Image (spheres, coloured by chain):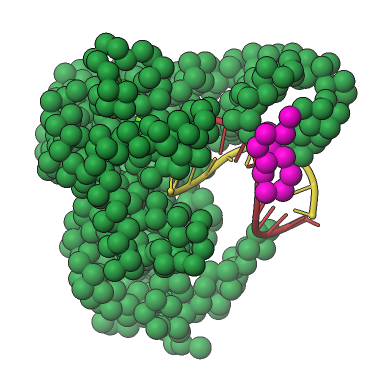
Chain colours: A green, B red, C yellow
Amino acid sequence: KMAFTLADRVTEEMLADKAALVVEVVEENYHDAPIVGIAVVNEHGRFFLRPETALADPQFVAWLGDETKKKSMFDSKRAAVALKWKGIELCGVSFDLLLAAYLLDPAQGVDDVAAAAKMKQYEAVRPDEAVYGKGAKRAVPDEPVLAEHLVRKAAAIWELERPFLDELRRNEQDRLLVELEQPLSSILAEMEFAGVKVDTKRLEQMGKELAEQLGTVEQRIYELAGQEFNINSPKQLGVILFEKLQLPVLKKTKTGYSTSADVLEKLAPYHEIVENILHYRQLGKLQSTYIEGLLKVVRPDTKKVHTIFNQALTQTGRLSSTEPNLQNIPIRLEEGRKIRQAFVPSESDWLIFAADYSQIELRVLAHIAEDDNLMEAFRRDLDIHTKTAMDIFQVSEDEVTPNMRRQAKAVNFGIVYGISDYGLAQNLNISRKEAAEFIERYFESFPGVKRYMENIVQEAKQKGYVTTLLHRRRYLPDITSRNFNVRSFAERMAMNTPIQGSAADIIKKAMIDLNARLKEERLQAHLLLQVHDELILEAPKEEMERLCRLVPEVMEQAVTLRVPLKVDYHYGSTWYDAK
DNA sequence: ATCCGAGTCAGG
DNA sequence: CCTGACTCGG
Ligand SMILES: Nc1nc2c(ncn2[C@H]2C[C@H](O)[C@@H](COP(=O)(O)OP(=O)(O)OP(=O)(O)O)O2)c(=O)[nH]1
Ligand SMILES: [Ca+2]
Ligand SMILES: [Ca+2]
């Protein structure tokens, strides 16, 4: 047991201009949830306050909003939003222990202070699972244990602040935490709290048609299958297809036989049920995930949806979006995209405005690779897909049929991570002999992409890690693995990580430089979303002319590469219409 | 119950 | 290559 004042009230010696602060949201989704406890640690001691009391105090609430009071926490963003929900603001966070651990070694998957502490040999603090538990397991314990815990954390944060910073500084990532991640964290905070408005009525009439649509196919499947079965269980389905209907087994999952859309395109010719199955899956994924899914989570009063961008999960520096995931709304098949029509501004007479990097990930290859061909393609603003098709067929700026392009494109999608001939051949539905025969041609057509791939794999061998434009790391012990396929995975990570990685650094940065301008220019615009390479804003309809310059200007100039980045922008009265 | 793992597919 | 949500079913 470790002692601390167990406060009933706020003494001012809790308001020192530097403290580790802990603000416990024990709910798994932080949006509008109970704050269960608050521990503060400072030069004057270690204190515990109950939220009810604490949150009422104009003295405390004041200290919180003060950017001159420096706090140190773990996942300030969790506390930030939870507090924004209470109309309380949180400023002057100087060190976030979650973001730090995450830059040191994202693979450790640090989810709580206990994890962060292992890293630096500190152990007088307990995991979350130990105090709370797993599933229907997780519960809020009594104050005695709670106080003890929130303090032990806060204590650790105070303690680990400089051990952590010293390794970042040694690692060459001091300005990644300070200038990049922490600034962004605030920004995501606002974004998640702003929310995006959904048109629940249109979502309702989309679902309405899809059930009638779906009933229909369902029946047809059962008709031609000869019997009923749960189509969704592919274990049950394969039995219908490859046993009772006697069909060729072409691909195979590690368990039994495979029914991935890839195999079905191939089985189509073989029997009329095949395409009915594909239709059924597509229609059903809309309804399950983008109708019943979203509608399950609009906030009923405001009609908005509040995502959580997880700044500290991905192994390569992307963000992720959870519950719901606004980073995978349909856009590819035309009927899918209609969903986007349900994403509307939150103010009458405002517009969604959306801008994105053209080929960001490739452009980064070009810059990191220092291949001449690719650098020139981007500098002359050539349609990079069209130039690719040319180079792999050795043909003209018009002898490119549309199919030669669906092919060139797919290379550019995989050459960002050393795609396998086998792997490629899958997406393209071709013979593996042709897959590598396009690969072969790409490489002699862009042999600076070849070197890089050679080189990066060997730097990974030397250093045990790769890095990115802004010095994010990724360790890769499996690089020297005994085992062909494991060494191989690790070798594509070896080469792809600096690409995904910089691409993400660059946009995270664009977002900071953006908030920065909008705030100076007194503008009403604010970011709603990030989808890996686009930004989505809502602004007053009288503000587009500006954003059309501003947003591209700031995005393009976010960093400086041996290629010019390229941005596209569109705005409409909905997401669908900004395309 | 309740957890986890694969599967499939939506996006990058 | 990097995710996540929904789904069955060991
Ligand atoms: N990794 C991956 N990303 C894809 C794939 N297909 C589409 N994308 C995503 C990644 C890009 O950020 C985004 C670019 O949009 P498009 O697919 O329409 O390509 P783009 O507009 O650059 O070319 P286009 O103008 O359509 O000829 O799409 C794929 O097969 N793999
Ligand atoms: Ca395009
Ligand atoms: Ca895109």
Highlighted magenta segment, given as a residue range: A248-259
- Classified by dominant secondary structure, the portion drawn in magenta counts as loop
Q: Is residue A408 visible?
A: yes
At 30% from the left and 39% from the top, the residue drawn is A443
Q: Is residue A374 left or right of residue A422?
A: left
Residue A247 percent location from the top left of the image: 77, 27
In this orientation, which residue lies closer to the viewer: A501 or A384? A384
Q: Is residue A563 magenta?
A: no
Q: Is residue A68 left or right of residue A216?
A: left
Residue A559 percent location from the top left of the image: 15, 44
The answer to whether A7 is drawn above or below residue A502 in the figure is below
At 63% from the left and 24% from the top, the residue drawn is A266
At 46% from the left and 87% from the top, the residue drawn is A2
Q: Is residue A47 visible?
A: no
The answer to whether A61 is drawn above or below residue A119 in the figure is above
Which picture quadrant has residue A290?
A: top right
In this orientation, which residue lies closer to the viewer: A480 or A569? A480
Q: Is residue A249 magenta?
A: yes
Count of marks placed on residues = 0
Q: Quadrant of the C terminus of chain A?
A: top left
At 38% from the left and 32% from the top, the residue drawn is A438
In this orientation, which residue lies closer to the viewer: A27 or A5? A27
Residue A186 percent location from the top left of the image: 29, 50
Q: Is residue A153 left or right of residue A28?
A: left
Residue A89 percent location from the top left of the image: 31, 52
In this orientation, which residue lies closer to the viewer: A451 or A239? A451
The answer to whether A412 is drawn above or below residue A200 in the figure is below
Q: Is residue A27 left or right of residue A12?
A: right
